[PDB]
Length: 35
RNA sequence: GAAUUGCUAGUAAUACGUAAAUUAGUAUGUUACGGUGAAUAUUCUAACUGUUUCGCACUAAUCACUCAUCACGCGUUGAAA
View (cartoon, rainbow, N blue to C red):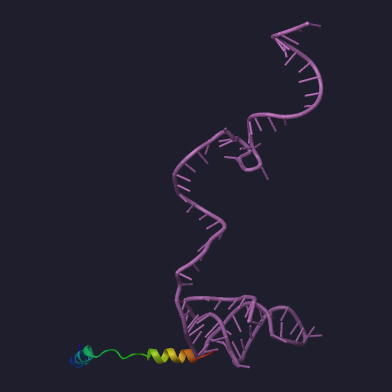
């Protein structure tokens, strides 16, 4: 592995994975949705 | 309001369309095709099935089998004025 990409991986070691969606808002919109 | 349909799923739903079969002609039916795309949680009840316990005089097997009744005769034995 290159050092720049090792540094990138080190930086992302600590970061939590961002959420795909807001589960509560997803639930509410799916409750609004029809058809 | 009785009533009823379907129930994790690319399913339901969709004032989403598209195609084909059957036709000379007619689809709101059928079968295909993709687009968008959810919700909910199952205390309960259960025919029926499979193991089982026990009983059994049934064995063509309970619509079973034995027992008893009623009549018809043919016998046998007993008591007898």
